[PDB]
Image: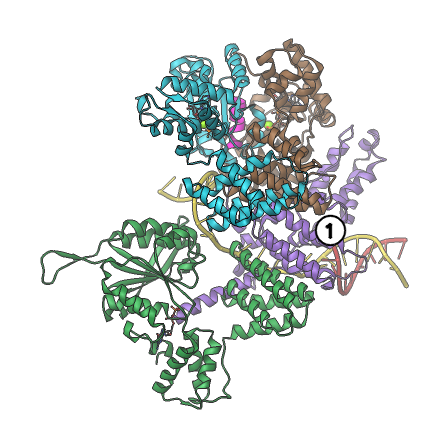
Chain colours: A purple, B cyan, C green, D brown, E red, F yellow
Amino acid sequence: NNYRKFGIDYTFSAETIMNKEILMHPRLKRIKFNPINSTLLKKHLKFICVQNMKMLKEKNKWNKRQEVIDYIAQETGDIRSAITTLQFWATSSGSLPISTRESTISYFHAIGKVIHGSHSTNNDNEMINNLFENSNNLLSKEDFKLGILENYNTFNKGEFSISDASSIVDCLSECDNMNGLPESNEYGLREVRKTFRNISKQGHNHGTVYFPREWKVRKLQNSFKVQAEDWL
Amino acid sequence: SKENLPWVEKYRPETLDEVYGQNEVITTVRKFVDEGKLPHLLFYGPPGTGKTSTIVALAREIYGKNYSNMVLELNASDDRGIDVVRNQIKDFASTRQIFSKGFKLIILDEADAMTNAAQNALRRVIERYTKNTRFCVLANYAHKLTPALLSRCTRFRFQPLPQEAIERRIANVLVHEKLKLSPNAEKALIELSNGDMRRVLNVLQSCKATLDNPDEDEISDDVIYECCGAPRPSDLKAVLKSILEDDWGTAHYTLNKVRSAKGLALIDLIEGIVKILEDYELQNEETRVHLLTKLADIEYSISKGGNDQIQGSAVIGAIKASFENET
Amino acid sequence: MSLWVDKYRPKSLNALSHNEELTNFLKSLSDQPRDLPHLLLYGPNGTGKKTRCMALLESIFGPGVYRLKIDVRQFVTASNRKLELNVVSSPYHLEITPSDMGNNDRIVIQELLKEVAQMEQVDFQDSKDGLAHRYKCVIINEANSLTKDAQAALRRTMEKYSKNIRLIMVCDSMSPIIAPIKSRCLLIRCPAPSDSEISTILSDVVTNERIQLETKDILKRIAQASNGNLRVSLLMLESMALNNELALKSSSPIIKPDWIIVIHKLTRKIVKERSVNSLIECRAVLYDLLAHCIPANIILKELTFSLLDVETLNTTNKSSIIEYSSVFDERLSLGNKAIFHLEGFIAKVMCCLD
Amino acid sequence: LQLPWVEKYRPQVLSDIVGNKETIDRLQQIAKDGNMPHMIISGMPGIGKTTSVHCLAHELLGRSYADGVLELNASDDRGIDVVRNQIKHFAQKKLHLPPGKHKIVILDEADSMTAGAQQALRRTMELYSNSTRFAFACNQSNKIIEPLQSRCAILRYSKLSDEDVLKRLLQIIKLEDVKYTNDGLEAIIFTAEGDMRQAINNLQSTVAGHGLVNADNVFKIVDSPHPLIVKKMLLASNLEDSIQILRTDLWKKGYSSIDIVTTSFRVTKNLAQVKESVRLEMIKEIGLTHMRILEGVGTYLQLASMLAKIHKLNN
DNA sequence: CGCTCCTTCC
DNA sequence: GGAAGGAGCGTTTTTTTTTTTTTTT
Ligand SMILES: Nc1ncnc2c1ncn2[C@@H]1O[C@H](COP(=O)(O)OP(=O)(O)OP(O)(O)=S)[C@@H](O)[C@H]1O
Ligand SMILES: Nc1ncnc2c1ncn2[C@@H]1O[C@H](COP(=O)(O)OP(=O)(O)OP(O)(O)=S)[C@@H](O)[C@H]1O
Ligand SMILES: Nc1nc2c(ncn2[C@@H]2O[C@H](COP(=O)(O)OP(=O)(O)O)[C@@H](O)[C@H]2O)c(=O)[nH]1
Ligand SMILES: [Mg+2]
Ligand SMILES: [Mg+2]
């Protein structure tokens, strides 16, 4: 029902809600929060389980509290979601697969997943399928291909064969000619992942990833257009 | 009135008995209406197979001659956005019949052109008002239909029209007109139809026009090819034989002469040659790979225009190079 | 004062000094301009196509065609994206560059040109009885850069309203022109001037400006450095004369466009080193070039031929280079972002050299 | 008249829903206890999500169902104004209910809700959770914004097994006194592809057409899922076998080229046997053929060339 | 996801 | 005096057609 490609309809964040002047105003202070870490979440889940020791012991789930607490801690950084999941598990006499709310991955996290792969998953096909199923909005945007193009050199601080870089860049060039079909994005990401997995080694030191600089070029082009119109 | 109509419309089936080729679907739907247990329907198939005709005939049979008063028909020519689904379709499906004539019917022709949001809104409208209303969705491309909508509809596939049904309809048309069709002309018409009745009727009308005196002149295969400007099988066979046996100069001259004799287009020659080669028994499979890939590339290039002579020479060279593998 | 490119620009067909056969053909066209067909002039950039079109118009109408003024026309898209276009006008003709509108060029064809085509130009007769009718002349600059939709929109406008309008399109290459538009036009090939004619024009300019020239060879060198672009030849002549106190000498350096020198440096860097880091620096250079609005295809041409000019490379290297250049030129034509294809070309060249 | 069996035999109690035994049992526990939390129900079409939520609401609220349930789906207005007025007033209503019972807001097809409405729902959930509980039903749980997911228990419904579908089909057959054979029920289950709605529709169609549910009678009307045919076409070890499958089973049956290529891409995404390089190359070829089809060249020759390229890659 | 510094825990 | 865990960094944002929601009207 939206069919709109503006910033706000894509992401709900301070940048899309506020503007540059407000954020950079000297009288406004911005503090960024991180997901609650495993230690604090585990501590508070144990506290809650202790507060409900009687019912847990009566239901015979007290002995298994540590297992579910540890699983919940590694699955989310949302305290409310963790508490809700714990309540759902404890109040259940039967056994069900414990699951929390899904968490989206960031842009640089997706770039890192494509370049280096995922620790949890060893099958690249499964990783790519999950990435496209859950992060379609991020992958579809054309800035992701530009990010891959501008960051693939970070692998081993750019100490791999020119042949692999040529293969990756040629694949991206071919994908740019596919009118933005999903097959194009899938093929590009799969090519990058396969190429980097073919040369992955323990003794590698990687570089720093950066956002693509196309926006700077666009601004410079606009300034050039204004100057050229003045000259004309 | 009907006499002035194009044949594709003048010969539109009025009753289900006039629909040919889809025996299984017609049988099942007729029994469903006989028992009055019609479910939500999906008619999936390629162009000109009888979907719209079948649904209109079924509506006529259910409601007799007054079907226009209790049937809501919508197609791609009408706006069918989410607002339309929420207001118009919803109100029609949620209101009583004109004279308590059982259930109401909503036909969504060419529903593959509807937006995802409208299709999503349709789910609960279909589900909640099933007692009073039944939906019919017609489509040629299933991938445009959301999974939820597909799950809700009983699916019927309209196959490409078999040869026998086309022959029967051609006989009916020939009797209705004062026309005479030769067996070879009928075979050519069936071959070029590709299972679409509309093409059959249009070509028949053009052939009747081509005749100087249709009251006594008979349509032959030559008339069909003249009307369609299509190559004859002999032309295709000669071109292929020259390509596979004669030298480059002779093959080029043969192709040029065959095309210039009747102004044949290269795409139709390629399609006929592909049909011929599909039945060829090749001992080397790599030959098939080369043939298919190169000819598909040539067809795609022709689709955008380009140089005709270069494309013809490319076809010749591609066939020769591919068949060098069989050596 | 005005630049020498415009100061000594010929203002009539008789003033043209190179490609005599083309001048004769244009004069034959001007003999009976009553039934002049639509024209499409194609040839290398900077050869004098626009000058010849203006000379033809002057022959048909008169010197007043050079009394040009500028107007701004506003267009609104289906998304309410207001924008503007510059329309140059003389009492007898109009000049537009719809390609400056990007993908919106079609709007210009659908709204402006059509309206111009529909409004029939009539005027009271000074001496005779009744109104007199005259067709309007419209020049479409950078015709080859129009989108296929705009070119399609041109067709029936050209055909139906042939009584009121006559189009003169100018392009540097006819490859991007759709077949129907070419079919609707009289095609005129405009060859570039030879080195001798460029040298003669430059010598006439030098004599007019009273610039001391040690030897005529300098002019020849200037010609050989312009690659047949007369406008560039005159610009470099003026720059060199000003930079040398209006005294040219055999030792005076030839001034070339800065981006050309940058591309030469990039070619040398590519030849010298072939590695990932070299590729990243090449990306930086390419982005710097693109920031100045240099077209991607132009960059690809200049880089390709600069690479082909390297003496150390062998036949296989150059053959592979030209193959990759053709492939990536097609990819640029069919692509959306040029950086991918330029990077791919450079990476392929690095692989083939190494 | 006579209702279609899909609606006639819609389960009215939680004990008549087959499959997802663990989830259905937990729902029964919630119904008997009362402490229903905010919940999200996700799964593929036609597996019982809507039926499960409706049955749970009915069991929980008893006679108070009419005044204690607010149902809204994609067919109703669900914009930000609706959240501001109708849902807010319903959640503000003071209704006397038995201990452990709360008002229920059912939001079917919650995925389609607009971003503004979803963001507005946060505050109403925060304020009126003591008296109101929300049950979202969707096909993609990820289409509900994270702040809303943070407040709800997640429940994912899996595809129904052949055993559960067979059990429900047998119950329906016994109720309708339908004559059948084992092969016929096997064919119905195989063609349903885990969708109970499709299984019931196909059974009803077969019974209406012929009454006796055999394999041949079922396959006269029902077609084998074309994804499996496409998988067979792609996995054929011989080019001629792939071409023969494409011709006989797909092209001459009236399947459009666009559908064939889209299904080929979907199937190739899930081929476990093949290597990653081969898979990505096949995806590239499928994408190029799809581009050609979208431009208007949707011919059988293009699909044959796609198959030839795929076979070349397999070698 | 990888790299670079401050705790935190034994 | 070994890691184990954690935080912070690595960022910016129009445009073709077409559909849809929202707010004021
Ligand atoms: N089974 C058929 N029997 C007799 N005539 C048919 C049949 N199918 C198509 N025709 C003829 O072709 C014309 C068009 O038939 P339609 O029912 O409109 O085909 P269609 O399948 O609905 O085409 P699409 O999918 O909307 S392009 C009819 O008026 C008939 O004259
Ligand atoms: N587990 C099931 N047990 C019995 N019947 C089922 C079951 N699932 C689906 N059905 C039947 O199919 C019909 C539809 O079931 P639903 O609950 O609406 O499926 P659904 O998962 O909600 O589909 P969506 O997500 O709205 S497309 C029911 O009336 C039942 O007759
Ligand atoms: N003396 C002389 N100058 C010419 C002639 N033709 C072109 N020029 C000049 O050389 C420049 C050519 O640039 P231009 O007219 O823009 O050619 P275009 O870019 O191909 O259309 C102009 O500055 C002209 O003044 C000619 O025949 N004689
Ligand atoms: Mg139809
Ligand atoms: Mg449902």
**With respect to residue D156, does A9 lie above or below?**
below
Relative image position of residue D285 (x, y in whole percent): 62, 45
Relative image position of residue A66 (x, y in whole percent): 83, 40
Residue B86 lies in the magenta stretch: no
Residue beneath the point at 47% across and 67% down:
A223
Q: Quadrant of ligand 3?
A: bottom left
**With respect to residue C310, does C181 lie above or below?**
above
Residue beneath the point at 47% across and 64% down:
A222
| Residue in front for this viewpoint, B298 or D21 | B298
For mark 1, what is the residue? Answer: A117
Give the quarter of the image for residue D242. Answer: top right
| Residue in front for this viewpoint, C68 or C227 | C227
Relative image position of residue A107 (x, y in whole percent): 64, 53
For the question of whether residue C33 can be seen, the reply is yes
Helix, strand, or loop for circle 1? Answer: loop
**Of all residues shown, which one is farthest toward the top?**
D177
Give the quarter of the image for residue C272. Answer: bottom right
**With respect to residue B6, does A70 lie above or below?**
below
> Label 1: chain?
A
| Image side of residue B117 versus residue D266, left or right | left
Residue B124 lies in the magenta stretch: yes
| Residue in front for this viewpoint, B305 or A110 | B305
